[PDB]
Amino acid sequence: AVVASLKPLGFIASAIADGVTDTQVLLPDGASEHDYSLRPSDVKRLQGADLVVWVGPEMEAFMEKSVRNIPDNKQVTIAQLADVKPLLMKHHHGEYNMHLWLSPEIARATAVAIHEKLVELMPQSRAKLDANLKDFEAQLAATDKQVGNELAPLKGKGYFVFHDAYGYYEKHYGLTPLGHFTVNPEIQPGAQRLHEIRTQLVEQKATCVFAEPQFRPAVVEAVARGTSVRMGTLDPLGTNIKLGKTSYSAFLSQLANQYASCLKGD
Ligand SMILES: O=C(NO)c1cn(Cc2ccccc2Cl)cc1-c1ccccc1
Ligand SMILES: [Zn+2]
């Protein structure tokens, strides 16, 4: 099996590995990067993998140690790929945005790297692997066209998010975020912080404020209350999407729908 650290990396790997080997996701969606410690059973899975796919030590810091013993020809470390360097832009404490799965261009380079490793590891399946890469790139191009068109009429509409993640996706499709607020998903900001957030919401003319699935509706409402800003939800992990050949294209389209759902009209 190919073992991917995070679900959207699973989406990409499952496009390339389809009909060749299973794709597995290491961690449940609810986990994170610095508090999370790997179970010995997780380490075993990594070492048993045909191929490990992860962003790298600036993102899944918790697995850097586990991945040292795995040979280079059995891992794709996305942040360290040669073709990914010119695609990086300025796990949140590092210098670069490491939410790399949100860049269609980085997804493409990831798929190429996965394909290349798999062909070396499983040359008996080269043709199927070539076919899978061909199909992934064709879907990505088609999705890219479709999403770009869905999001084009939304240009210029401002919004805030509770997570500085989406820059790769927003720059690529020409969305115009105003900025981000650090908000605890379980606990609303204090009186002073909330005042400052709410005034920026109105002052900067935001159409929407976007939360994520793990935010308690109460804290989102507390942020949006009084302002005339519509509330939205973005899911940067596509938690509801199953692994499979078409999953990464489905993820990019679902994210567009989530943006559009709050942003369009008014
Ligand atoms: O980037 C982030 N935090 O700053 C994330 C945001 N999420 C969204 C999320 C968290 C918990 C449960 C569901 C979801 Cl969609 C997941 C991560 C995340 C997951 C694994 C590793 C690092 C981050
Ligand atoms: Zn993040």
Image (spheres, grey):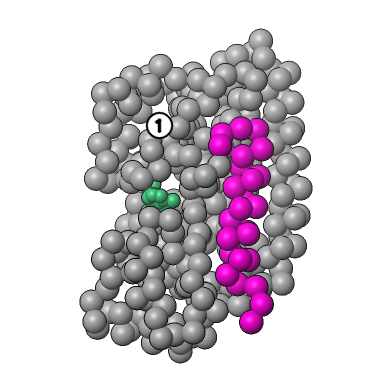
- Residue marked by disc 1: 26
Q: Residue furthest front?
A: 218
Q: Quadrant of the C terminus?
A: bottom right
Q: Residue furthest top?
A: 124
Q: Position of residue 3 (x, y in %)?
A: 46, 27
Above or below, comparing residue 86 to residue 115 in the picture: below
Q: Kindly identify the residue that appears in the image at 70 percent across and 28 percent down.
A: 132
* Other residues around mark 1 within 10 Å, as few (<14) / some (14–19) / many (≥20): many
Q: Position of residue 192 (x, y in %)?
A: 24, 83
The residue type indicated by label 1 comes to Leu
Q: Please tell me whether residue 125 belongs to the stretch shown in magenta.
A: no
On whether ligand 1 comes within 8 Å of the CB at mark 1, the answer is no
Q: Please tell me whether residue 256 belongs to the stretch shown in magenta.
A: yes
Q: Secondary structure at mark 1?
A: loop
Residue 138: in sight, yes or no?
A: yes
- The chief SS type of the magenta part is helix
Q: Nearer the viewer, residue 100 or 13?
A: 13
The magenta segment:
242-266
Q: Kindly identify the residue that appears in the image at 38 percent across and 38 percent down.
A: 28
Looking at the image, how many numbered discs can be counted on the residues?
A: 1
With 147 as the anchor, is 160 left or right in this view?
left
Q: Position of residue 52 (x, y in %)?
A: 46, 27
Residue 109: in sight, yes or no?
A: no
Above or below, comparing residue 36 to residue 4 in the picture: below
Q: Kindly identify the residue that appears in the image at 71 percent across and 20 percent down.
A: 128
Instruction: Residue 155: name its quadrant.
Output: bottom right
With 195 as the anchor, is 53 left or right in this view?
right
Q: Nearer the viewer, residue 239 or 177?
A: 239
Instruction: Residue 158: name its quadrant.
Output: bottom right
Q: Position of residue 151 (x, y in %)?
A: 68, 65
Q: Nearer the viewer, residue 18 or 79?
A: 18
